[PDB]
Structures are given as C-alpha cells and as structure tokens.
Amino acid sequence: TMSLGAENSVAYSNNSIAIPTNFTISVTTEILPVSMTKTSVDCTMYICG
Amino acid sequence: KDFGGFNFSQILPDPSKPSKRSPIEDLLFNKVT
Ligand SMILES: *[C@@H]1O[C@H](CO)[C@@H](O[C@@H]2O[C@H](CO)[C@@H](O)[C@H](O)[C@H]2NC(C)=O)[C@H](O)[C@H]1NC(C)=O
Ligand SMILES: *[C@@H]1O[C@H](CO)[C@@H](O[C@@H]2O[C@H](CO)[C@@H](O)[C@H](O)[C@H]2NC(C)=O)[C@H](O)[C@H]1NC(C)=O
Ligand SMILES: *[C@@H]1O[C@H](CO)[C@@H](O[C@@H]2O[C@H](CO)[C@@H](O)[C@H](O)[C@H]2NC(C)=O)[C@H](O)[C@H]1NC(C)=O
C-alpha cells in the first residue's frame, strides 16, 4: 500500500511563529510540449495508390 | 483546536467516522449516487 508522504506534525501554538534564517536558490525544470510532427496524408493515394 | 475562535470542525476529519472524512466531505459522498 503506497505511502502518501512523510508524516510531519506542525508545532502549532497560539503564540509561536517560525521565521526563516536562511534561503536556498532552487532551480527546477518544467518540460512542456509545444508542437507535433506536421503529417499530411494523401487520402486518395493512401486508399488507392 | 485553539485557533482564536475559528472553527474548522465541519472541514476537518471526523474521528467518530470510520471513513475519516469531514462532515462536509461525508455529505458530499452521500449526495453523489
Ligand atoms: C519549535 O518548537 C517545537 C516544540 O517546542 C518543535 O517541535 C518538536 O520537534 C521535535 C523534533 O522534531 C519533535 O520530537 C517534537 O515532537 C516536536 N513537538 C511538537 C509539539 O511538535 C519544533 O521542532 C521547533 N521548531 C524548530 C524550527 O526548531
Ligand atoms: C546559509 O546557508 C548557506 C548555505 O546555503 C551557508 O553557507 C555555508 O557556510 C558554511 C560555513 O561557513 C560553509 O562551510 C559552506 O561552504 C557555505 N555554503 C555555501 C554554499 O556558501 C551560510 O553560512 C548560511 N548562513 C546562515 C546565517 O546560517
Ligand atoms: C465548533 O463547531 C462545532 C459544530 O459547529 C461545535 O460542536 C457543537 O457543540 C455544541 C455545544 O458544545 C453542541 O450542542 C452541538 O451539538 C455541537 N455540534 C456538532 C455538529 O457536533 C463545537 O462546539 C465548536 N467549537 C469547538 C471548539 O469545537
């Protein structure tokens, strides 16, 4: 049975905050298709030659 | 559930239900046939 994620319990309280003291410059890739191969079929030649 | 007066019981999961769904989610699953 597949796990959904690592279990994290957020330390919530009514008067506590978490402030970052540092940062990471993260570069991620996103691949998106744009076009296909332009195909033309001669219908008469395909059916009959 | 001390959120400064904000109540999320209708959207948080219900421990009493075996399906662990919220009351709103339980109603949504009952209303779709
Ligand atoms: C902020 O404080 C809370 C509690 O003082 C920390 O939460 C605990 O983290 C330890 C280590 O992972 C756990 O074993 C405890 O169960 C956590 N307690 C609660 C109530 O969640 C939290 O890690 C602290 N935040 C930072 C950034 O140090
Ligand atoms: C914030 O994080 C960076 C890493 O992203 C820290 O830079 C590192 O510092 C240690 C100790 O001086 C070096 O050994 C590493 O080589 C550093 N890494 C890089 C990429 O420069 C930086 O010190 C952190 N700053 C604070 C205030 O925590
Ligand atoms: C959050 O909302 C729920 C429901 O809206 C509250 O539960 C009601 O509590 C009263 C008295 O405690 C009961 O008479 C109702 O029957 C309860 N309704 C349900 C659906 O359980 C709840 O008290 C509110 N507050 C908190 C802190 O959870």
Image (cartoon, coloured by chain):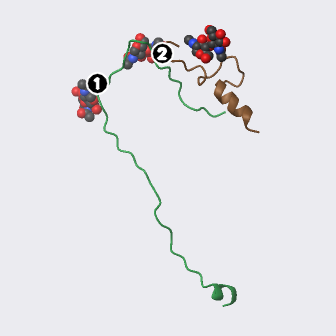
Chain colours: A green, B brown
Frontmost of labels 1 and 2 is 2
Neighbour tally class for label 2: few under 14, some 14-19, many 20 plus, Cα within 10 Å: few
Residue B19 in percent (x, y) is at 70, 25
Residue sitting farthest toward the right: B33
Neighbour tally class for label 1: few under 14, some 14-19, many 20 plus, Cα within 10 Å: few
Task: From the image, tell me which residue sits under label 2.
Answer: B3
Left or right, A21 with reference to B1: left
Seen in the picture, residue A16 relative to A32 is either above or below; the reply is: above
Left or right, B16 with reference to A40: right
Left or right, A35 with reference to A22: right
Residues behind callouts 1 and 2 on a single chain: no
Residue B26 in percent (x, y) is at 69, 28
Q: CA distance from mark 1 to mark 2?
A: 26 Å
What residue is drawn where x is 73% and y is 38%? B32
The answer to whether residue B21 shows anywhere in this view is no
Label 2 element class: loop
The answer to whether residue B31 shows anywhere in this view is yes
Seen in the picture, residue A49 relative to A41 is either above or below; the reply is: below
Q: Of residues A15 and A39, which is closer to you in this image?
A: A15
Residue type, mark 1 in image: Thr
Is ligand 2 less than 8 Å from the beta carbon at label 1? yes
**Mark carried by residue B27:** none
What residue is drawn where x is 51% and y is 74%? A38
What residue is drawn where x is 59% and y is 19%? B9
| Quarter the C terminus of chain B occupies | top right
Residue A6 in percent (x, y) is at 53, 28
**Mark carried by residue A21:** 1
Number of marks drawn: 2
